[PDB]
Image 1 (tube, rainbow, N blue to C red):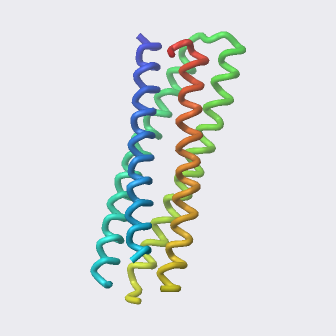
Image 2 (image 1 turned 120 degrees about the vertical axis):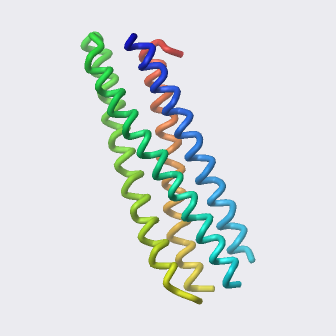
Length: 159
Protein backbone atom coordinates (compact mmCIF):
# COMPACT_ATOMS: atom_id res chain seq x y z
CA UNK A 1 0.00 0.00 0.00
CA UNK A 2 0.95 3.66 -0.27
CA UNK A 3 0.42 4.91 3.30
CA UNK A 4 2.40 1.94 4.63
CA UNK A 5 5.28 3.03 2.39
CA UNK A 6 4.68 6.61 3.57
CA UNK A 7 5.16 5.44 7.16
CA UNK A 8 8.29 3.47 6.22
CA UNK A 9 9.83 6.43 4.41
CA UNK A 10 9.21 8.85 7.28
CA UNK A 11 10.62 6.50 9.95
CA UNK A 12 13.68 5.77 7.80
CA UNK A 13 14.20 9.53 7.33
CA UNK A 14 14.10 9.93 11.11
CA UNK A 15 16.70 7.19 11.59
CA UNK A 16 18.96 8.78 8.97
CA UNK A 17 18.73 12.24 10.54
CA UNK A 18 19.55 10.77 13.99
CA UNK A 19 22.64 9.06 12.54
CA UNK A 20 23.82 12.39 10.99
CA UNK A 21 23.32 14.18 14.37
CA UNK A 22 25.47 11.56 16.15
CA UNK A 23 28.22 11.95 13.50
CA UNK A 24 28.11 15.79 13.85
CA UNK A 25 28.32 15.40 17.66
CA UNK A 26 31.24 12.95 17.33
CA UNK A 27 32.98 15.44 15.03
CA UNK A 28 32.43 18.31 17.47
CA UNK A 29 33.77 16.18 20.32
CA UNK A 30 36.95 15.24 18.46
CA UNK A 31 37.58 18.82 17.28
CA UNK A 32 37.10 20.19 20.80
CA UNK A 33 39.49 17.49 22.05
CA UNK A 34 42.20 18.42 19.53
CA UNK A 35 42.00 22.18 20.04
CA UNK A 36 42.15 21.89 23.84
CA UNK A 37 45.60 20.29 23.31
CA UNK A 38 51.51 18.17 16.91
CA UNK A 39 51.55 17.40 13.18
CA UNK A 40 50.17 13.85 13.23
CA UNK A 41 47.45 14.85 15.71
CA UNK A 42 46.15 17.41 13.20
CA UNK A 43 46.50 14.89 10.36
CA UNK A 44 44.37 12.40 12.30
CA UNK A 45 41.68 14.92 13.24
CA UNK A 46 41.55 16.03 9.60
CA UNK A 47 41.11 12.39 8.53
CA UNK A 48 38.38 11.74 11.09
CA UNK A 49 36.64 14.96 10.06
CA UNK A 50 36.75 13.94 6.39
CA UNK A 51 35.35 10.51 7.32
CA UNK A 52 32.46 12.16 9.16
CA UNK A 53 31.91 14.45 6.16
CA UNK A 54 31.80 11.54 3.70
CA UNK A 55 29.33 9.66 5.90
CA UNK A 56 27.13 12.74 6.18
CA UNK A 57 27.10 13.28 2.39
CA UNK A 58 26.05 9.64 1.87
CA UNK A 59 23.24 10.01 4.39
CA UNK A 60 22.06 13.30 2.81
CA UNK A 61 22.07 11.64 -0.61
CA UNK A 62 19.84 8.85 0.68
CA UNK A 63 17.59 11.40 2.38
CA UNK A 64 17.16 13.38 -0.87
CA UNK A 65 16.20 10.18 -2.64
CA UNK A 66 13.68 9.40 0.13
CA UNK A 67 12.28 12.92 0.06
CA UNK A 68 11.64 12.61 -3.69
CA UNK A 69 9.83 9.31 -3.13
CA UNK A 70 7.83 10.90 -0.27
CA UNK A 71 6.75 13.81 -2.48
CA UNK A 72 5.65 11.44 -5.25
CA UNK A 73 3.65 9.30 -2.80
CA UNK A 74 1.94 12.33 -1.26
CA UNK A 75 1.04 13.52 -4.77
CA UNK A 76 -0.59 10.18 -5.61
CA UNK A 77 -2.56 9.82 -2.35
CA UNK A 78 -5.96 11.55 -2.64
CA UNK A 79 -5.56 13.75 0.43
CA UNK A 80 -8.14 16.38 1.23
CA UNK A 81 -7.27 19.88 0.06
CA UNK A 82 -6.51 21.17 3.58
CA UNK A 83 -4.29 18.25 4.52
CA UNK A 84 -2.52 18.40 1.16
CA UNK A 85 -1.82 22.10 1.83
CA UNK A 86 -0.42 21.38 5.30
CA UNK A 87 1.83 18.60 3.96
CA UNK A 88 3.02 20.88 1.14
CA UNK A 89 4.05 23.66 3.58
CA UNK A 90 6.14 21.18 5.60
CA UNK A 91 7.79 19.60 2.50
CA UNK A 92 8.60 23.11 1.15
CA UNK A 93 10.30 23.83 4.47
CA UNK A 94 12.14 20.48 4.35
CA UNK A 95 13.43 21.21 0.84
CA UNK A 96 14.67 24.62 2.00
CA UNK A 97 16.40 22.89 4.95
CA UNK A 98 18.04 20.19 2.77
CA UNK A 99 19.32 22.93 0.47
CA UNK A 100 20.80 24.81 3.43
CA UNK A 101 22.47 21.60 4.60
CA UNK A 102 23.92 20.87 1.17
CA UNK A 103 25.41 24.36 0.84
CA UNK A 104 26.82 24.06 4.38
CA UNK A 105 28.49 20.74 3.64
CA UNK A 106 29.99 22.08 0.41
CA UNK A 107 31.45 25.03 2.37
CA UNK A 108 32.87 22.63 4.99
CA UNK A 109 34.44 20.41 2.31
CA UNK A 110 36.15 23.37 0.63
CA UNK A 111 37.43 24.64 3.98
CA UNK A 112 38.88 21.22 4.86
CA UNK A 113 40.55 20.94 1.45
CA UNK A 114 42.19 24.34 1.94
CA UNK A 115 43.36 23.54 5.47
CA UNK A 116 44.97 20.32 4.24
CA UNK A 117 47.58 22.30 2.28
CA UNK A 118 49.05 24.15 5.26
CA UNK A 119 51.59 22.76 7.72
CA UNK A 120 51.45 25.17 10.68
CA UNK A 121 47.53 28.44 17.10
CA UNK A 122 45.82 31.43 15.38
CA UNK A 123 45.70 29.88 11.87
CA UNK A 124 44.33 26.52 13.07
CA UNK A 125 42.00 28.24 15.55
CA UNK A 126 40.54 30.44 12.84
CA UNK A 127 39.88 27.30 10.80
CA UNK A 128 38.31 25.83 13.95
CA UNK A 129 36.14 28.94 14.40
CA UNK A 130 34.67 28.54 10.92
CA UNK A 131 34.08 24.80 11.35
CA UNK A 132 32.49 25.44 14.77
CA UNK A 133 29.95 27.79 13.26
CA UNK A 134 29.21 25.42 10.38
CA UNK A 135 28.69 22.43 12.75
CA UNK A 136 26.43 24.48 15.01
CA UNK A 137 24.23 25.50 12.10
CA UNK A 138 24.13 21.90 10.79
CA UNK A 139 22.97 20.66 14.20
CA UNK A 140 20.18 23.26 14.14
CA UNK A 141 19.07 22.20 10.63
CA UNK A 142 19.05 18.53 11.70
CA UNK A 143 16.93 19.29 14.75
CA UNK A 144 14.44 21.25 12.65
CA UNK A 145 14.29 18.28 10.24
CA UNK A 146 13.58 15.86 13.12
CA UNK A 147 10.78 18.14 14.26
CA UNK A 148 9.19 18.45 10.83
CA UNK A 149 9.31 14.66 10.31
CA UNK A 150 7.45 14.23 13.59
CA UNK A 151 5.00 16.89 12.42
CA UNK A 152 4.39 14.99 9.17
CA UNK A 153 3.71 11.79 11.12
CA UNK A 154 1.23 13.68 13.32
CA UNK A 155 -0.56 15.41 10.41
CA UNK A 156 -1.03 12.01 8.73
CA UNK A 157 -2.26 10.31 11.90
CA UNK A 158 0.63 7.84 11.76
CA UNK A 159 1.93 8.50 15.29
